[PDB]
Amino acid sequence: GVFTFEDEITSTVPPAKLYNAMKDADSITPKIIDDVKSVEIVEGNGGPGTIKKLTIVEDGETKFILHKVESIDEANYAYNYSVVGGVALPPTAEKITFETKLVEGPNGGSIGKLTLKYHTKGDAKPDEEELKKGKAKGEGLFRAIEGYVLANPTQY
Ligand code: NA
Image (spheres, rainbow, N blue to C red):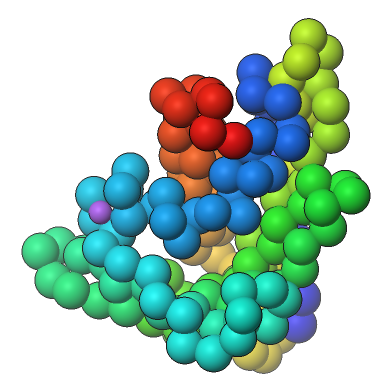
């Protein structure tokens, strides 16, 4: 079944810049996250439905994570993707979706909503430790991208 979790977040970066940076995560992520070595497209043009393979290092071991691009709403500053395979996917989960949606915040920044949707296999529910890890993945990426934009303000 489906279990949704939402976190509100803020940034001093305006939402157009963050949104462009999020759209370039394939490029940015390997540079700024040490453990991410590469992002490769398996099928698609980059837009919704595209399947990607991330190569990472975990505990000194090379591993893969599979992503699927879900949605892109430019108008609403929205970028959505799912984990569909690999170590970031718990065995009790079919998939975990990570949505990010931004609006204008006071004084030129952004107000964010990060959403995790866990599609479970059975009636089984996400446990607490797995929710922690999902939130850390979701927010960690958002903050990483944010940090890149704070360091390269003219780029986006
Ligand atoms: Na890296």
